[PDB]
């Protein structure tokens, strides 16, 4: 019963992760030394790299589960799971930054065109990567049995991370996306033709975020410490992992393919 | 196009001084400036090089540490701060402008020079002639020797020729092996191949008499040679 | 331009009227001869070995 | 009378057509038979010049086959070293609307002109270390569409005011003015011996001019739409023309008639620039469909394509020794094919 | 490194040239380029006299925004050969004088020009700021004579408001495609002050649309 369902979920996660890192690698390839004068490509390139790392970590973790061991496997598995969570956190950060940039492009168009520093994207991404690495290193060093399995400190660092995520990433992302929606509905949609494509892609982005990317964060941060009954933690973990794998596999489609102005 | 240089004078050993040269009449900020030394009795010695935009800066092995080179592009001035002056540093310093692109003529202009008195690997480029006497209307052929091949893999041989008429700064005659500069008569003609090179003058006049120097630009530091004086 | 323009056009056409002409077979043969004469010195026609190519790498 | 003058003109045109078709013993294709074709030759891009930030509209090679000048709508004239992709010079322009650039055979000057109705001559080799304007050749009442150097002192400039002109750079005046060309003339191509020059206009008519006499020696027709590209054959006795009809036409000065037309059903886009390979066996044409086609001059077939451009190929040129062909484009990229 | 010393200095100079080219391009990308258009003596002087031979380019600033407006009316040549040079402008400032409906008819020529330009294959997605100036002269002419003085297709009232609205509708109906570009219309005269603001709102709208097309929502 539950074992067969778990096998099915793992197989689907493996196949979707294969498709995901294929798509992410293609997106990084198509954004190399070109397609970068547009201020909406450094974020997408960084997100493609982060999602590639995240989905590769998923596929590797599933492969390690299919070939379990005792001692040598455990340490590389722990390190690369920490890598997966680091990539997850940085991908969420990049989604939030992308949505905020999209909102600010229409809220302040004069500033976005003739006042925004050309490298502001670059060092914003650098700061995001640095902060995510710092927080994930702290969480791994206070949560991994390899270095320090301090249960109280693991819980404290997880609570801090969850508070920061649910008080910054989700509110700012949702608010920026909704503000873009409302502003283009009440400022341009009335006079010209209503931009239905804008509305549909914005709603799709918020939907896929809130119901595919958050699940893993909320699970691995809060549900890991709410003393869930047995035979229930597996279901939530697998559902969250599959949802995040689907979100990271579909992020290139919803961000680069829909937005290929030059290649169309 | 003139390069008037200032500063200098009598400095006690171990002291400090700041050489200056003000550029005018040309696009100073696009030229890579040099400093070249000449002892009161010896030939020319290369001191320092600064590129356009203050990028690569070079010093000779004998000047490193206590010599520093700097430029002020808005002020149209080139500086050379010197500290801990040794007895071998008494010489006359020339400010030399140079620009580097395909087909250009480096070292095309030299400053008037300033004097400095103090109280008291490399490419060997020497020529085995000196104080050659010759009469106007004849033909001369002075030659220069290089330690190794000056022919680069791109096909360019980096050998320059300079004439220093007495009482005035040296001027460029040949800005690469077989490349005549601007303003010099067609009688001059550099030549050579491989390792050995020479300079020939078909019908010399009475005013093109002086010390002739062969210099290399293949590698840094830039090594001149001992002169080949010409007289009546 | 009421009268002088048309006369100028007629004169210009007369100028091209007196131009000598040669059979186009001869001109085509001459073009083919020139094309087959300088065929060796045609680097775009014949890719030379990379030793002489200055755009190799 | 006016009716008499028109009838005389029509009779003259009919007589000229009869004389033209009398000498047409055979076409080039019929003669060029039982001969090995050039073959499906394909070339690979060797360099990629990546400095411009707007549409590139003109390029011209140097006589040394090393230097290269390109013009673009960002108000920049860049001189390139094609061997190393080094930027020798980058010349700002007062007017960013330029459609042609010229490179002197002596290499001391460049010329560029466009919608500002002025041809500017720039001094490459100065005592100071910069590039400076020498003279501005005002005197045309339209946009300048082409310009070529006869020598350091004579330059011939086409224009959008239906006229070509020859200029004396030192005095800045037109020594001779070439008129009698309905519609704006879009291109010109000096003879290899620099005693004649052809020019194609919007009336689909290509005229051959005498530089000293100042009179149109011959006039050629056959294009259905306006003419954008023109270039002399290396032999000097022929020249090719590119028009909006998606057709390239080979003419002949000594026959006064068209030799053959280079076209394909799959090609409907206009032709931007044309040039000849050394020995005149290949015809290199730039198109609107982002691609350059290698036309075999003797036959009427495509020797090969090169593509490699994401936008319209606006200009192209071949070196004096035939080492390489450089193509400009509207994507701000130059490619040195070999 | 297989490079001579002068080769290295050449690459350094080339890199300095590259830096200057990048700076120039980044400075140009923060500029709005407008294509002024319309028949001569059609109020073009009035709309160009608010602030600041071939193309007569003007540069003006408003609310920390820089405009590069180009006048190409004096070209007097085949437009189709050089019109693609202006593809990619922010907007077209098309100027039409209302009073030139009887002065062989200027309004028909202006309508033909507007139909030719607004429907150009290069400009299928650029907004058009249709300036309709000389409205006081239109007032005086309508007081002297109705619009039906030369046009029998009109059947409405002989008042300034309705006639101006009819002309605006006739102009705005010339474009086949209303689903790809926005036509902005304004009424001005010799002495206006808010005319400079209308182009600011138009360019702000097209800037927003450009950003949306960049991110790919549009
Ligand atoms: C509080 C923890 C870190 C906060 C992370 C915030 C990430 C989103 C906000 C920064 C991105 C948007 C900044 C503007 C970038 C742009 O539009 O170019
Ligand atoms: C860290 C986030 C970066 C975003 C900074 C927003 C700066 C806005 C500056 C004022 C907006 C000016 C642009 C339009 C002019 C206006 O406000 O009316
Ligand atoms: C392991 C984390 C590394 C920390 C730094 C991450 C930086 C990623 C790259 C961000 C910028 C990439 C391209 C920016 C260049 C540009 O501004 O055009």
Image (tube, rainbow, N blue to C red):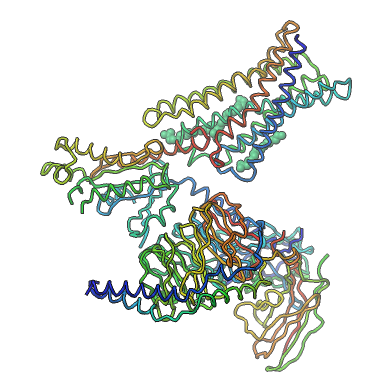
In this view of the protein, which residue sits in the foreground, A256 or B111? A256
Q: Is residue D131 above or below residue E180?
A: below
In x, y percent, where is residue A73? 86, 24
Q: In which quarter of the image is the N terminus of chain E?
A: bottom right
State which quadrant residue B22 falls in: bottom right
User: Is C44 placed above or below E86 here?
Assistant: below
Q: Is residue E40 visible?
A: yes
Q: Against A29, is D247 above or below? A: below
Q: Which residue occupies the foreground of this view, A158 or A218?
A: A218
Residue E98 quadrant: top left
Q: Can residue B76 be seen in this view?
A: no
Instruction: Judge from the rendering whether residue D245 lies leftward or rightward of residue B102; answer left or right.
Output: left
Answer with the quarter of the image where residue D85 lies: bottom right
Residue B105: give x, y in percent of width and height: 64, 71
Q: How many marks?
A: 0
* Residue extending farthest right: A71
On screen, residue E88 versus residue A10, left or right, reads left
Q: Which residue lies furthest to the left in this view?
A: E144
Q: In this view, does D278 lie to the left or right of C13?
A: right
Percent x, y of residue B210:
70, 84
Q: In the image, D228: left or right of A39?
A: left
* Front one among A212 and B195: A212
Residue drawn at the location 63% of the way across and 34% of the way down = A125
Out of D141 and A163, give the one closest to the viewer.
D141
Q: Which percent across, then down, holds residue D306?
A: 61, 55
């Amino acid at each position: 019963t539950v074992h067969t369902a778990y096998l099915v979920l793992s197989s689907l996660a493996m196949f979707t992760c294969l498709c995901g890192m294929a798509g992410n690698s293609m997106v990084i390839w198509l954004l190399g030394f070109r397609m970068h004068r547009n201020p909406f490509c450094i974020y997408i390139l960084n997100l493609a790299a982060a999602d590639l790392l995240f989905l590769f970590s998923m596929a590797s973790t599933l492969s390690l589960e299919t070939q379990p061991l005792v001692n040598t496997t455990d340490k590389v598995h722990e390190l690369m799971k920490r890598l997966m969570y680091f990539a997850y956190t940085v991908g969420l950060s990049l989604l939030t930054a992308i949505s905020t940039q999209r909102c600010l492009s229409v809220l302040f168009p004069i500033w976005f065109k003739c006042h925004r520093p050309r490298h502001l994207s670059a060092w914003v991404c650098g700061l995001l990567w640095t902060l995510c690495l710092l927080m994930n290193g702290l969480t791994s060093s206070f949560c991994s049995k390899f270095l320090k399995f301090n249960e109280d400190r693991c819980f404290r660092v997880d609570m801090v991370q969850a508070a920061l995520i649910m008080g910054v990433l989700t509110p700012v992302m949702t608010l920026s996306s909704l503000t873009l929606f409302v502003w283009v509905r009440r400022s341009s949609q009335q006079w010209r033709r209503q931009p239905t494509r804008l509305f549909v892609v914005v709603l799709a982005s918020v939907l896929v975020f809130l119901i595919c990317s958050l699940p893993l964060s909320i699970y691995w941060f809060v549900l890991y410490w709410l003393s869930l009954p047995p035979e229930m933690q597996v279901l939530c973990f697998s559902l969250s992992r599959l949802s995040s794998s689907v979100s990271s596999s579909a992020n290139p489609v919803i961000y680069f393919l829909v937005g290929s102005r030059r290649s169309h | 196009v003139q390069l008037v240089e200032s500063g200098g004078g009598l400095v006690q050993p171990g002291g400090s001084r700041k050489l200056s040269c003000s550029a005018s009449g040309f696009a100073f900020s696009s030229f890579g400036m040099h400093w070249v030394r000449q002892a009161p009795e010896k030939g020319l010695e290369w001191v320092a090089y600064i590129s356009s935009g203050s990028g690569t800066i070079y010093y000779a092995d004998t000047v490193k540490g206590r010599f520093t080179i700097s430029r002020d592009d808005p002020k149209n001035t080139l500086f050379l701060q010197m500290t801990s002056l040794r007895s071998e540093d008494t010489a006359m310093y020339y400010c030399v402008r140079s620009i580097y692109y395909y087909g250009s003529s480096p070292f095309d202009f030299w400053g008037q020079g300033t004097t400095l008195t103090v109280s008291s690997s490399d490419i060997v480029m020497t020529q085995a002639t000196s104080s050659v006497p010759v009469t106007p209307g004849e033909s001369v052929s002075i030659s220069c020797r290089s330690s190794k091949s000056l022919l680069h893999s791109n096909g360019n041989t980096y050998l320059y020729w300079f004439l220093q008429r007495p009482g005035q700064s040296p001027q460029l005659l040949i800005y690469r092996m077989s490349n005549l500069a601007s303003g010099v008569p067609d009688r001059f003609s550099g030549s050579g191949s491989g390792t050995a090179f020479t300079l020939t003058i078909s019908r010399l006049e009475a005013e093109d008499v002086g010390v002739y120097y062969c210099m290399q630009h293949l590698e840094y530091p830039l090594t001149f040679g001992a002169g080949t004086k010409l007289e009546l | 331009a009421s009268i002088a323009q048309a006369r100028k056009l007629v004169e210009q056409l007369k100028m091209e009227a007196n131009i000598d002409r040669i059979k186009v077979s001869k001109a085509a043969a001459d073009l083919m001869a020139y094309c087959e004469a300088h065929a060796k010195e045609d680097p775009l026609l014949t890719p030379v070995p990379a030793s002489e190519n200055p755009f190799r790498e | 009378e006016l009716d008499q003058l028109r009838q005389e003109a029509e009779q003259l045109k009919n007589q000229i057509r009869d004389a033209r078709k009398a000498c047409a013993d055979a076409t080039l294709s019929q003669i060029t038979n039982n001969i090995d074709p050039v073959g499906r030759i394909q070339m690979r891009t060797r360099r990629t010049l990546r400095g411009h930030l707007a549409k590139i509209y003109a390029m011209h090679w140097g006589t040394d086959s090393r230097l290269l000048v390109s013009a673009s709508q960002d108000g920049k004239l860049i001189i390139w070293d094609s061997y190393t992709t080094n930027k020798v010079h980058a010349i700002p322009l007062r007017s960013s609307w330029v459609m042609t650039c010229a490179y002197a055979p002596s290499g001391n000057y460049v010329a560029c002109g466009g919608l500002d109705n002025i041809c500017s001559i720039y001094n490459l080799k100065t005592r100071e270390g910069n590039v400076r304007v020498s003279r501005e050749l005002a005197g045309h009442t339209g946009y300048l569409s082409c310009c070529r150097f006869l020598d350091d002192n004579q330059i011939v400039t086409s224009s959008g005011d239906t006229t070509c002109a020859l200029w004396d750079i030192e005095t800045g005046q037109q020594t001779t003015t070439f008129t009698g060309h309905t519609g704006d003339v879009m291109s010109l191509s000096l003879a290899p011996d620099t005693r004649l020059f052809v020019s194609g206009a919007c009336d689909a008519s290509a005229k051959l001019w005498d530089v000293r006499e100042g009179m149109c020696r011959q006039t050629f027709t056959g294009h259905e739409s306006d003419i954008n590209a023109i270039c002399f054959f290396p032999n000097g006795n022929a020249f090719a023309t590119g028009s909006d009809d998606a057709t390239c036409r080979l003419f002949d000065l000594r026959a006064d008639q068209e030799l053959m037309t280079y076209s394909h059903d799959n090609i409907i886009c206009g032709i931007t620039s044309v040039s000849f390979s050394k020995s005149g066996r290949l015809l290199l044409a730039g198109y609107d469909d982002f691609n350059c086609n290698v036309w075999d001059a003797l036959k009427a077939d495509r020797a090969g394509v090169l593509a490699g451009h994401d936008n319209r190929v606006s200009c192209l040129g071949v070196t004096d020794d035939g080492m390489a062909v450089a193509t400009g484009s509207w994507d701000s990229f130059l490619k040195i094919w070999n | 490194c297989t490079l001579s010393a002068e080769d290295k200095a050449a690459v350094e100079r080339s890199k300095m040239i590259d830096r200057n080219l990048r700076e120039d391009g980044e400075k140009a990308a923060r500029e709005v380029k407008l294509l002024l258009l319309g028949a001569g003596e059609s109020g073009k002087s009035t709309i160009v006299k608010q602030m600041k031979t071939g193309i007569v380019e003007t540069h003006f600033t408003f609310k920390d925004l820089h405009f590069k407006m180009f006048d190409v009316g004096a070209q007097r040549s085949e437009r189709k050969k050089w019109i693609h040079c202006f593809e990619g402008v922010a907007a077209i400032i098309f100027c039409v004088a209302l009073s030139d409906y009887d002065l062989m008819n200027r309004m028909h020529e202006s309508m033909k020009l507007f139909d030719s330009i607004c429907n150009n294959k290069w400009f299928t997605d650029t907004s058009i700021i249709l300036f309709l100036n000389k409205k006081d002269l239109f007032e005086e002419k309508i007081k002297k004579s109705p619009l039906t003085i030369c046009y029998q297709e009109y059947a409405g009232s002989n008042t300034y408001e309705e006639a101006a609205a009819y002309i605006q509708c006739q102009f705005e109906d010339l474009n086949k495609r209303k689903d790809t570009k926005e036509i902005y219309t304004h009424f001005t005269c010799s002495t206006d002050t808010k005319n400079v603001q209308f182009v600011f709102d138009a360019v702000t709208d097209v800037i927003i649309k450009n950003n949306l097309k960049d991110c790919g929502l549009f």
